[PDB]
Amino acid sequence: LTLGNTTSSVILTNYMDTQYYGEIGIGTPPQTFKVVFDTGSSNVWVPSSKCSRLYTACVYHKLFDASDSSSYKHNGTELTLRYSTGTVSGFLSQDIITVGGITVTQMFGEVTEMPALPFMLAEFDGVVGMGFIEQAIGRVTPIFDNIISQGVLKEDVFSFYYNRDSQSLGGQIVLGGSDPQHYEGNFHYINLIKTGVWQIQMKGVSVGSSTLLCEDGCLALVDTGASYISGSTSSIEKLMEALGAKKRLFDYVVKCNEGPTLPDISFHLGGKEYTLTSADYVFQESYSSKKLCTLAIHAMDIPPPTGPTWALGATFIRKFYTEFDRRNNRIGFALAR
Ligand SMILES: Cc1ccc(S(=O)(=O)N[C@H]2CNC[C@@H](C(=O)NCC3c4ccccc4Oc4ccccc43)C2)cc1
Ligand SMILES: *[C@@H]1O[C@H](CO)[C@@H](O)[C@H](O)[C@H]1NC(C)=O
């Protein structure tokens, strides 16, 4: 392991408080893609020019053309990548990737099968996995491991800032450090249960003053690629009953006029309570008694080995600026500015 002095940053675009994406350049000359930086996965993928136009998601997204890149190195190995909302498949390729002004030779997936549900809803083209090699499909070296290998970064850390929707900064990723302009106070660290996954121990979930859930302890995946806070179907049913929310097909809702009256939700992580008020978890679209307002908390049954687990996504990161520490296998949280 080599350390330099360089800190690099990627400006993110906030789409509806659900999608935070930045830009990467792939190839020579660079082909630009809108990408989500996901701590819950470890593969890099973008849609391929080899994607059949009968996949409508491929008509609506930027496609990587290897035939236009002079730095491209063929691989051809087939791979399937499974997410919570859907699945993508294609093959592996190698090329130069630029992310925050850091140029790295990276093995990535060229997606040839991209389903309209959910990919037509995606403002981003692809994904940049910020997880560990242990989660990488095809044991492909992740981009952050390749960036560490260069020995340019001041520290083996990366930090996430997700803003509240607005013509301001959507968010920001710092490679090799943190940005003090985006947090206040000091970081409180929670060690990873084990290397290989950005997952920490959770000591309890409170609805108001009472610790209703996770009383005997549970898991919390700190996931930048997840839009919401998620728990198991069972945990979410208890949580929603306590809030007074109604289950719909894809989400939970409350009558808009009752959004501001909902109790605080607290997450016990390390030696601290991480509290979200209703303003932090309700999509307060109106105050009308004749309208339904969505919550930024969903049921998600994450399969083993990673799951059953809670996932602390954009809902959580908006309130708490997050530092992912590779050198010490820990996650730091500080109050976001
Ligand atoms: C079945 C299954 C459940 C859960 C998981 S997991 O371990 O929790 N994986 C997570 C890792 N972080 C991102 C999660 C996710 O899909 N977020 C949703 C987000 C996304 C992020 C990355 C890739 C694809 C992807 O699809 C869309 C499409 C439209 C809008 C938003 C997204 C899945 C894997 C597989
Ligand atoms: C594809 O890449 C892997 C490394 O990730 C390598 O071991 C393998 O030999 C490559 N295959 C081809 C056909 O180049």
Image (tube, rainbow, N blue to C red):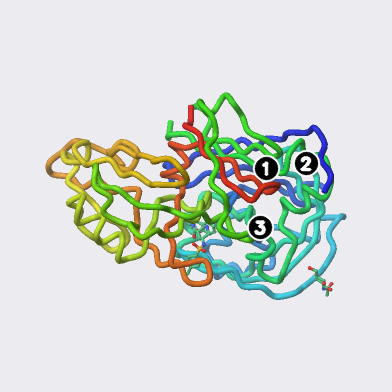
Q: Hey, which residue is sitting farthest bottom in the picture?
A: 78
Type of amino acid under label 1: Val
Quadrant hosting residue 251: bottom left
Residue at which label 1 appears: 157
Q: Nearer the viewer, residue 94 or 140?
A: 140
Sequence order check: which comes first, mark 1 or mark 2?
2
Is the residue marked 1 within 8 Å of ligand 1, measured from its CB?
no
- Badge 1 marks a residue whose secondary structure is strand
Q: Nearer the viewer, residue 74 or 248?
A: 248
Q: Position of residue 228 (x, y in %)?
A: 41, 51
Q: Which residue is depicted at the point 38% across and 46% down? A: 267
- Callout 3 secondary element: loop
Q: Is residue 92 left or right of residue 112?
A: right
Q: Which residue is located at x 52 percent, y 37 percent?
A: 188
Residue found 48% across the figure and 27% down from its top: 337
Residue drawn at point x = 17 percent, y = 41 percent: 258
Which residue carries the number 2 mark? 102
Q: Nearer the viewer, mark 3 or mark 1?
A: 1
- Per the image, the residue denoted by label 3 is 63
Name the amino acid type tagged 3.
Leu
